[PDB]
Amino acid sequence: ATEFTPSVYSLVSKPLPSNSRPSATLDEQAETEDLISQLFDLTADPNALVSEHGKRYSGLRKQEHTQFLASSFFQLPGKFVSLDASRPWLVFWTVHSLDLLGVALDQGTKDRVVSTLLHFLSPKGGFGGGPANSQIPHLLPTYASVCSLAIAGNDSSTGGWKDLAAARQSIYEFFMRCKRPDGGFVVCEGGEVDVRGTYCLLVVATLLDIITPELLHNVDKFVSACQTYEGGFACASFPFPEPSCRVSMAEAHGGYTSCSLNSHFLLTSVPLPSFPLSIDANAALRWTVLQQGEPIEGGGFRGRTNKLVDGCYSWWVGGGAPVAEELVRREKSRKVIPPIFNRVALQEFTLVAAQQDPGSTGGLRDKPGKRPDQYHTCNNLSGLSIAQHKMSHSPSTVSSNRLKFDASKGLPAVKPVAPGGGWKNEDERQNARREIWANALGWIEEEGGEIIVGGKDNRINTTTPVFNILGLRLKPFINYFYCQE
Amino acid sequence: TYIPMSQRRSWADVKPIMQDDGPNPVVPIMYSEEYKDAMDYFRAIAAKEEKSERALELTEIIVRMNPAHYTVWQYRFSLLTSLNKSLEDELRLMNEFAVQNLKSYQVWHHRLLLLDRISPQDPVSEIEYIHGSLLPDPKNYHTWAYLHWLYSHFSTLGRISEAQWGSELDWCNEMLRVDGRNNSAWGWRWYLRVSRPGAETSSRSLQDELIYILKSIHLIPHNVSAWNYLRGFLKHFSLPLVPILPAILPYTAFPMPSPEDTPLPVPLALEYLADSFIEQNRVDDAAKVFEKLSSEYDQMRAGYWEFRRRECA
Ligand SMILES: Cn1cnc(S(=O)(=O)N(CCN(Cc2cncn2C)c2ccc(C#N)cc2)Cc2ccccc2)c1
Ligand SMILES: CC(C)=CCC/C(C)=C/CC/C(C)=C/COP(=O)(O)OP(=O)(O)O
Ligand SMILES: OC[C@@H]1O[C@@](CO)(O[C@H]2O[C@H](CO)[C@@H](O)[C@@H](O)[C@@H]2O)[C@@H](O)[C@H]1O
Ligand SMILES: OC[C@@H]1O[C@@](CO)(O[C@H]2O[C@H](CO)[C@@H](O)[C@@H](O)[C@@H]2O)[C@@H](O)[C@H]1O
Ligand SMILES: OC[C@@H]1O[C@@](CO)(O[C@H]2O[C@H](CO)[C@@H](O)[C@@H](O)[C@@H]2O)[C@@H](O)[C@H]1O
Ligand SMILES: O=S(=O)(O)C[C@@H](O)CNC1CCCCC1
Ligand SMILES: O=S(=O)(O)C[C@@H](O)CNC1CCCCC1
Ligand SMILES: O=S(=O)(O)C[C@H](O)CNC1CCCCC1
Ligand SMILES: [Zn+2]
């Protein structure tokens, strides 16, 4: 199982060569290499039986991380005002982290979570970063709120899911107001256009059964044109004047590559003709694996070429790996197994370098020398989950899903903004519903694919690629909105 | 001491509106007296949709405390357009924001909206500002994306001259001279030389580009940026790898290699050699180097190189 995933401790750690050419980049890289490698030297090898005397233990400090999240879950200091427009993310990072850590919230606290988020819902559609009387709707807190309701909510009258169901038409209309002709979405009224919006919108639209042809028009082209020469994806593409050509507007970045790969994947389950426009799957996989750092930097991921490793990219880049791998697999089958990244090294980065030092505040962090935060706690753990478990999109599971789908059950169809913006007829809508639902539930944990570095006490729960919530949350949630319970 | 807005006669007619959190909210923030008071009045102003000078001033107060407040930025831009305010003055205020370290997606997007609306005949001074902004912060993702948009938007209006494009390439070359490992500058080079609609792509132009890439590789052989650019260049223009192979071959053991602290082999030089074998239909020889990458020369990616090897065998 570990033949092609060597431990950081079993490899030679050497600096990135200078070639006698110093630069600001190399100065920063060498400094980071020192910070990480020294911590690895101070810490016992997680894989060892005789955990050597005097060295720091690298076990996942689950209770310390639970405390870190608990301490700021009910009250945040005034300095957190910089995140006042992002409070649904603070909810998401906490409740998803607790899910991964296997810590249950009581019903009273869950009810508080549901109540807090519902007040972020505006009647005109979508969630904002704060109460509806304070902030306008935005695609990003819409994703964070919807996912948090999947995690902490339920199907009772105080469970929040009922409220999401009633809001389906208005959320769809908000999505349509965000739409631009070139296939991009603004994140909010008068807001920026980027692929994070596309990802967030596509997740929510998939989960709530509000996908239509008019919502998706050109969306595939916008995403596909974000792919750079490096193989990863930038934030946006520019349409040169329907457009004569589309050009990527920046560097391949881990965050935007995650969003683009995931957006594309969600689009592949919509049965529209000549849709979605293809991406270069092999180039995206290549770019993904190349971002895994050298042994000296602990085998964590960086977000772009010649920048620094960072614990949060364990999710953004690492979590993109199974998606890219499946896309490559589908392309090869369209013409006609060892791990594709170092699953062990990534876990070692998390355990050794990304955890706060023991006996302190707890939480996980960007890198040694950086304060832990909720965002890094969530994304470190999400990445750790992807490395620990072998998540695959299973064609036979999708087939099973197709066989059990009940098309006579469902919530009322969304009314399109444009008269011809909907599905051609009921049969094609039901076929689409089936495909979207069946593929969303296609991710399975491979038997025998589990690798828990440091022993089974380090095991956390299995997050779903593309969605980033536990499968046990995803299933009943999406089943509720598709009436497949 | 702070004077509450409920005590100010300029605000006497406005009834503040409290944040509607509901009962016992999770993740509440202990807002400062100033911030809470400002938002209470912003909630009131925005609810009644007041477009006034005091409303404009209030939005500036808020974004200074929270530069990421997207709702307040949206309202501010509405105020600027409704009141027909000087958009040039607002640009200068944004310059002050950057100097005072107030930054986010929102400030850069605000700049974009201002420049879109101003729509200057010559955007040279804004280009210059961006260059100066990048010097102390040479990899700022948002700044690089904004530079792309600026040239892209204004080029469609036919407002970028050939001289202007020329000096941009000059500037890009200097950024790469200062730090050849600046991947952001490599990305800018790709726009200027390959992807932009007006890019010069004759046969000798592609020849010049190959000379530049190879010289960059020979200067810094372990520079992943240079290798990725090389690979992307050859792929985009469907150019064979074999004829260029003599320049890369030494790193596996047109400008040629000349450097101290250059341990061989370079992993991406091996990938090049492997892909050049696949080009020649030599699948066994390609598998052999992938195996070497997997087991000896790039073991972090052991599983990936094995995948590539199994694709041949
Ligand atoms: C370097 N970087 C990696 N991801 C991003 S981002 O997707 O644009 N994101 C993260 C910004 N970010 C800065 C950051 C992340 N990685 C390293 N840094 C310095 C951050 C946000 C929240 C917390 C907490 N608690 C701590 C740090 C901004 C964001 C803010 C609120 C909600 C969602 C995203 C930036
Ligand atoms: C759904 C959702 C919200 C997606 C998040 C996507 C995300 C992680 C985008 C990255 C944002 C980025 C351009 C910041 C890089 O900052 P940096 O220069 O400080 O980091 P770096 O040095 O690692 O590149
Ligand atoms: O590969 C299965 C693996 O074995 C377990 C023990 O049941 O962990 C061992 O293997 C890991 C990964 O190689 C090492 O870190 C050893 O220290 C550990 O004993 C289990 O966690 C499972 O994942
Ligand atoms: O920002 C000024 C304001 O925006 C408009 C639409 O452009 O209304 C939006 O802004 C208000 C106040 O923030 C909210 O109710 C939004 O939901 C609404 O879309 C416009 O009316 C103008 O007054
Ligand atoms: O210098 C020979 C070189 O060492 C190996 C490991 O045996 O690579 C290591 O050293 C390089 C520095 O040149 C770094 O990339 C390290 O990350 C790597 O572990 C081997 O590949 C060989 O080529
Ligand atoms: O696994 S964690 O590190 O999260 C939990 C942790 O640190 C608590 N250790 C106490 C210390 C006192 C004796 C009983 C155990
Ligand atoms: O992987 S196994 O399940 O075989 C063994 C395992 O979980 C060991 N965890 C230790 C136990 C003692 C305290 C520190 C953590
Ligand atoms: O659009 S709805 O009718 O659903 C609700 C609504 O308009 C609220 N506007 C607030 C006013 C204060 C600033 C943030 C937005
Ligand atoms: Zn980070």
Image (cartoon, coloured by chain):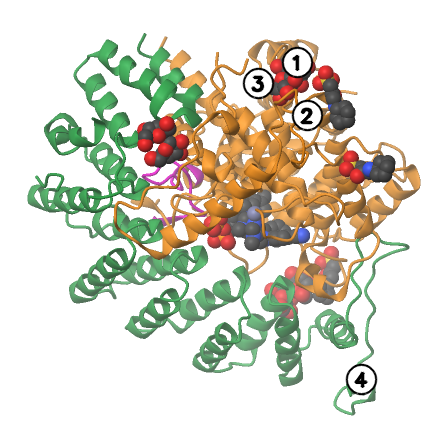
Chain colours: A orange, B green
* Cβ atoms under marks 1 and 4 closer than 8 Å: no
- Is A183 or A131 nearer to us in this picture? A131
- Residue A329 quadrant: top left
The residue where tag 2 is placed is: A462
The residue where tag 4 is placed is: B4
Chain for numbered disc 1: A
Q: Which residues are magenta?
A: A223-239
Amino acid of disc 2:
Thr
* Cβ atoms under marks 4 and 3 closer than 8 Å: no
The answer to whether marks 3 and 2 sit on the same chain is: yes
Name the residue rendered at 29%, 43% in the picture: B223
The residue where tag 1 is placed is: A401
A118 vs B287: above or below: below
Q: Earlier in the sequence, mark 1 or mark 3?
A: 3
The answer to whether marks 1 and 3 sit on the same chain is: yes
| Element type at mark 1 | helix
| Element type at mark 3 | strand
Name the residue rendered at 43%, 80% in the picture: B88
Amino acid of disc 3:
Ser
Chain for numbered disc 4: B
